[PDB]
Every structure is written in C-alpha cells, then in structure tokens.
Amino acid sequence: YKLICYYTSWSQYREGDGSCFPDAIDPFLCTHVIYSFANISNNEIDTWEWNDVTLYDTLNTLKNRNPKLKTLLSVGGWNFGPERFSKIASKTQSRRTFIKSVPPFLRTHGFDGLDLAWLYPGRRDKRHLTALVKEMKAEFAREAQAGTERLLLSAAVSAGKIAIDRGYDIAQISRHLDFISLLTYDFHGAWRQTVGHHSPLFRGNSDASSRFSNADYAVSYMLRLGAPANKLVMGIPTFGRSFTLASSKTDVGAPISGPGIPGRFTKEKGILAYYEICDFLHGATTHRFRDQQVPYATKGNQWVAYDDQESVKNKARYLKNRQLAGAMVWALDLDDFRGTFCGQNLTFPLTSAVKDVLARV
Ligand SMILES: CC(=O)N[C@@H]1[C@@H](O)[C@H](O[C@@H]2O[C@H](CO)[C@@H](O[C@@H]3O[C@H](CO)[C@@H](O[C@@H]4O[C@H](CO)[C@@H](O)[C@H](O)[C@H]4NC(C)=O)[C@H](O)[C@H]3NC(C)=O)[C@H](O)[C@H]2NC(C)=O)[C@@H](CO)O[C@H]1O
Ligand SMILES: *[C@@H]1O[C@H](CO)[C@@H](O[C@H]2O[C@H](CO)[C@@H](O[C@@H]3O[C@H](CO)[C@@H](O)[C@H](O)[C@@H]3O)[C@H](O)[C@H]2NC(C)=O)[C@H](O)[C@H]1NC(C)=O
C-alpha cells in the first residue's frame, strides 16, 4: 500500500514547538512525501518560499536514510488562484512552456515527481485539465529516454460530487496519472451556519440530503466513473475544523455564529492541528457520530470536528477493504510530529496509526 504524506512550506514559521522543518520527518513513516507548494512564474514552475531550495535539499536528504522513499513537489494549492491555472492550461503555448520547465526543475532539486493541486477546475476547464495531464505525462515518458527513472505524476482531486462532475474527466486523466489523491476531508460547506463533520466516513442514517458528503460516497462514485482502485488514494486529515456556537445547543444541527477561535500555534480561525486538539480535549466534552464514525468535542462555546487514532484506523481498514492503492495524509506538520502534546510518547500518532493498519495486509 502507498502512504502519501504532505509537508507544507509555511509550517516552518509557526512559533515554538509548532515550528516544523523537513528533518523532523521520520524517513520510514511514509512511502511518498509531497512538498507543498511550488508556484508558477512566467509560465514556469518556480520556488515559493525564500528558503525553498534549502528545504528541498533537507527533505530529499531523507532518501539517504530510506532509499525507497519517493518525493514529489506539488504545484498549486489554495493560495494559488485557480484562475491562474485556468489561464496557463487554456493556451497550448503557455501550457507547453510550463510542461517543458518541469523535468529540469525536479531533476535539479532531487524530486521524483510532480503533484498537481489545481483547486478547482471549473466547467470551462475540464477540457484543458485533460490536455495538461496527458501532455505532462507524455513529456515525462520522453524525458526518461535519457536513462533516468521516469518521473511520477499525481493529482489531488475534489471529493465533492458536484465539483467532480463539473471539472474533471476522471476516466481520461486516470490513465495518465500514477495516483489520484481524494480530498475526502472538506465535506462540511464553509457556506452554512450549522455544526457538522468535515470528514465523515459514512452517510449516517440520520439525514436524507447530502448523502454525497462522506468518504464512502466519493470513493464509490470515483470507482464508477472509471478510476482504477489501484490508483485511488483516500485523503485522511490530521487537522480538525472548529466552530463558535451561537447557542447552548451542542448536538447535530446546532446553530453556528462563525468559525472557532485560532489555535495558539496554527493561528488560523476555523482549523486546529491535531497536537492543538490534544491540548483542547483537556476539560472538553467528547462525542462520536456512530453513523459517520468520527468524533467531535466541545468546550465552552467552541465546537471541534476532528479525527483521532480510532477514526483514522477505521478509515484505513475501509480503504483496504475497497482495495484502494493507499492513504494520503494532510499533513505531517499538523500531526503531533514532536510527540509531546498527545500523551503517548509517540511521534506522528495519527499517521503512525494509519501505517500500522496498512502494514497488516
Ligand atoms: C488547514 C491548512 O493546512 N490549510 C492550508 C492553508 O492554511 C494554506 O494557506 C497558508 O496559510 C498559512 C498560515 O495561515 C500561510 O503561512 C504564512 O506563510 C508566509 C510565507 O509564504 C509567512 O511569511 C513569512 O514571514 C516571515 C516573518 O514572519 C518572513 O521571514 C518570510 O520572508 C515570510 N515569507 C514570505 C512570503 O516572504 C507567514 O509568516 C505565514 N503566516 C502564518 C499564518 O503563519 C501560508 O502562506 C498559506 N499557504 C500558501 C502556500 O499561501 C493553503 C495554502 O494554499 O493551503 C491549505 O492547506
Ligand atoms: C508566484 O508567481 C506569481 C506569478 O509570476 C508572482 O506574481 C507577481 O509577479 C511579479 C513579480 O513580483 C509581480 O510584478 C512584476 O514584477 C516586476 C518586478 O521585478 C515588475 O517590473 C513588473 O512591472 C511587475 O510589477 C506581479 O505583480 C505579480 N503577479 C500578479 C499578482 O499578477 C508571485 O509573486 C509568486 N509568488 C511568490 C510568493 O513568490
């Protein structure tokens, strides 16, 4: 099985223990580590952070400890305007320039492949996404003629049915991608004012509409659209989504006034790292949706939907039972990487729990 793990560039700036650099990563934990995110300047792939070349070097040195480890560089991300992707892919000329710049860049910095994170392709982009993937892969096949191992090509894809129907030709891109990571953790819409879990595994007998917003549905749908199980990887979150309650009601349906207050280290309203959640739990009230198989917690007027060792192991077994290629984790820097916040004298408790299940067969 594959265990795809993302590492984010901006995590280096978090204060104190929250600060995470590539060398904190256990070389034997994941099978693939993806660095997020690369930028595109003058239609060419390029660095993002001022010290990226140094961090690229630090990450790729892990391969001197674990020779089987593969690394990829992801282009795009949520702070990358999708309009920019749309513009590059729409014109055969700009598209070709970008494609041509990738192999040399990856080779120079020691990466084994490219991960595409266009979030998200609209109805008018579907056509061009296919061309982009097809042509990128053709370039990689051609570059391998030089005697070096062929570069890998992957893509992170929405798990939302409407988003999938709208911007992706799944059957077509599946044949050219080495693997596809399903973003099965952004299910509760940032649009409404209700409490809800962002990464439920199952539908849950307690609600008719949005039977589409759960991991099981997204996986089944992808398989029906033509994506081979051996290329599908299920996304598992290492963070939680928080809300500020509008009333004393804490159960399903409870009204929301807005996102939860920022975590001390992550400082982003709406989300908390797993290590911050481990601290939050002290004095909190824990619950678990039996139908969806995921937990949530509450303290004061703060409501948090998250994943723990149990739910993560649960998703990993589901994935194996469906014979998928493996799991993808977002993200290493949000798990208890130091292993000092979540009790168990264990580094990367969430990611390790996933690895354990995958190692069972
Ligand atoms: C849950 C989750 O992971 N969601 C992701 C989004 O959070 C993510 O958006 C990213 O948001 C983070 C934090 O909110 C943001 O981090 C900032 O990164 C910049 C660098 O790009 C830092 O700026 C540096 O400051 C120091 C001094 O303080 C300078 O020395 C340095 O030169 C600066 N860098 C630059 C630009 O020159 C900020 O300090 C840091 N701020 C925070 C909040 O700590 C990221 O930039 C956002 N990511 C990107 C790629 O823009 C979103 C990104 O796509 O993806 C989700 O996964
Ligand atoms: C990711 O790539 C972006 C696309 O190139 C880049 O956007 C910006 O690109 C240039 C460079 O800063 C900005 O302005 C130009 O810069 C030169 C100065 O060297 C000027 O002479 C020229 O007139 C022009 O102003 C753009 O304003 C900006 N592009 C936009 C917003 O359309 C991003 O900077 C890059 N991201 C990071 C963090 O590296």
Image: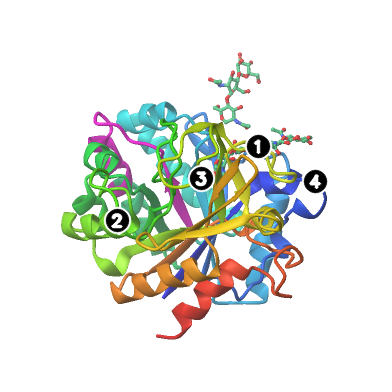
Q: Which mark is residue 203?
A: 2
| Real-space CA distance between mark 4 and mark 2, rounded to the nearest whole angstrom | 38 Å
| Real-space CA distance between mark 2 and mark 1, rounded to the nearest whole angstrom | 28 Å
In this view, the residue in front, 241 or 320, is 241
Can you tell which of label 4 and label 1 is closer to the viewer? 1
The amino acid marked with disc number 2 is Arg
| Residue 102 percent coordinates (x, y) | 48, 47
Q: Which mark is residue 15?
A: 4
Above or below, 140 against 81 in this view is below
Q: Which mark is residue 261?
A: 1
Q: Are marks 4 and 3 in contact (CB under 8 Å)?
A: no
Q: Quadrant of the N terminus?
A: bottom left
| Real-space CA distance between mark 2 and mark 3, rounded to the nearest whole angstrom | 20 Å
Span of residues in magenta: 113-134
| Residue 30 percent coordinates (x, y) | 55, 70
- The numbered mark, 4 or 3, whose residue comes first in the sequence reads 4
Q: Is residue 316 visible?
A: yes
